[PDB]
Image (cartoon, rainbow, N blue to C red):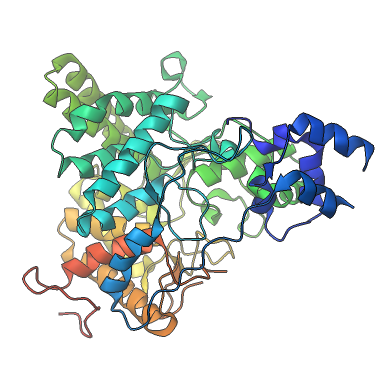
Length: 505
């Protein structure tokens, strides 16, 4: 169950990963022992051919499903036909030593070649399910996330043992809100698990003095309470073991454990990786996620607190509703006084090392508009910065730094397209909102026209190309989900489109 493979297999795990015995570091992270790892290990230490020894003692991950859809489908039919195809049930594990954490209900994976399910991308996958009326699948996934909250205290990065030490951008409260638009007391039903996740993020906050940090919560010098991304471990990621070992070796002037913590926590941020987190965008050894208060995360926390207040007011609990309402007020006040870059005119992360708000513009700047924490004048300023600097021919850019990392220029990511279009709409910036929507839709359609698939990310400098991208044609959750939602928006409800139309109106 809950012992991750790097502790389970000890030096054999570091030996197999270091030998580059497999092309993907994740492959051996998912290898299931055929017997007691204590036996395997004692076996290993005496009889030190490593490839044969591994094959005789582990069932490696099976070469997965290569689903081929029939050709000639429209973009919408293609997406809609894929929801059943990517529903999977992992009810039991193969043995006690399997890294896959079993889950109660069927869940929807981003792609057939995915071996587990993740947190924040599922919300955008769930937008598509909602759009195409798959409420049972949505309820199945919300049950799964509630189960994880009740069993592990939080939602792990994914349902793998080696993900238990970290979470991801906390969209659960918004999943419940989505489910609630169809099962109207989902918010009352899942308030206990919402409260428990909130406690996970705020763990230790009452004990904090100005200037202190603890796990995922910090307190600035003026008392302001904000959250940060944080992984509880500080070892190489089992699923990226040799990469992290080498990344820390590239910067021996800082303890490898700090580099590991910051690499793990950027994976928790969902932006793995990005110049957003790096002192030097060319050197991943300079990443310092845990010293950066993220503006998107704290927008999500504001939303979580407002939904907690609402979920309490609906249960008749006036004291609890009143408590979360004050917490959300303090959170909005802290976002506005610490995560706003006045000189540049946009929202931005806060630097714990320098105790200033940072200059870099990223697509995270749209998140306070998304959750309606921004004042109107700042929303208008973010929209001016968005069309001036981030809006590219194929959608909204992730950053303005082309670093080689994936959460950076020139890549556009479906969840950020949606967060931009919605946040801009929230404040009357319909023209920019529609520009983001139309350009990303054109990028997704044009890429579908040429590749007959959707992929995990798109190059926004043109239209028609994605990424190293997803190699099958059974393609990608949050792109599919966001595409359905946006495609509904650019045609009348009365006569929806199954393809992106030629001209924006």
